[PDB]
Amino acid sequence: VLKPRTLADLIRILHQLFAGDEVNVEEVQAIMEAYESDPTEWAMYAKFDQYRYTRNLVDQGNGKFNLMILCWGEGHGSSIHDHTNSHCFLKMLQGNLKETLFAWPDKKSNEMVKKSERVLRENQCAYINDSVGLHRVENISHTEPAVSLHLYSPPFDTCHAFDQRTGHKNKVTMTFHSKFGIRTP
Ligand SMILES: [Fe+3]
């Protein structure tokens, strides 16, 4: 497996693997995972908020993909959401996220069912698309933050949040807390 020595290396390798029309999911996953998280390389992107997790754009991938870092304050979690028909890779950079995989709801209303539950290990890279299922991810810690590196292809700025009690969903517009290390409006 090709091992990126820096975050910069990883970005460059990603620019190659997504330059084409096919993407080898397992290959990307392994190369993401092989990069050893180095806080010195990504602290410029680690901009936290007291109340919610933040999304911090790192690279726009020549429109082929978005690479972003997500910052999870203590106890922070996402809603149950989909991924708008894109590939979605998420790699741990610091701390640990619990991923809860959910099945899709019917038109009928009732409680959503868990298909899987795991903690992402150190440097681990996970993968999801809409055909895999829905998920919620959560900082496991109420005393330490978590930081993850996310890659989406194609890029997408809307998704759906799902009410665990009914399965009803809402369109959500996703925003960036910062881009290239610079706070956004
Ligand atoms: Fe997600």
Image: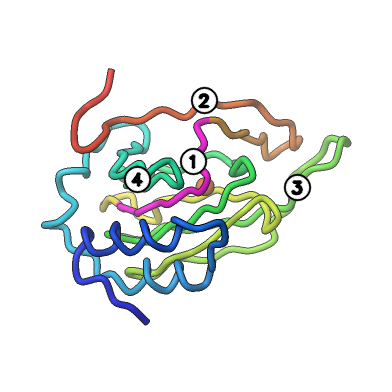
Name which of mark 2 and mark 3 comes first in the sequence.
3
Q: Whole-Å distance between the Cαs marked 1 and 4?
A: 11 Å
Kindly identify which numbered label has been placed on residue 104: 3
Query: For the view shown, which residue lies furthest in the top direction?
Result: 185
Is residue 67 magenta-colored? no
The range drawn in magenta is 146-157
Q: Position of residue 137 (x, y in %)?
A: 49, 50
Q: Is residue 72 above or below residue 169?
A: below
Name which of mark 1 and mark 3 comes first in the sequence.
3
Residue annotated with mark 2: 173
Dominant secondary structure (helix, strand or loop) of the stretch shown in magenta: strand
Q: Position of residue 177 (x, y in %)?
A: 31, 30
Q: Whole-Å distance between the Cαs marked 1 and 3?
A: 22 Å
Q: Whole-Å distance between the Cαs marked 4 and 2?
A: 16 Å
Query: For the view shown, which residue lies furthest in the left direction?
Result: 40
Colouring of the image: rainbow
Q: Position of residue 73 (x, y in %)?
A: 30, 43
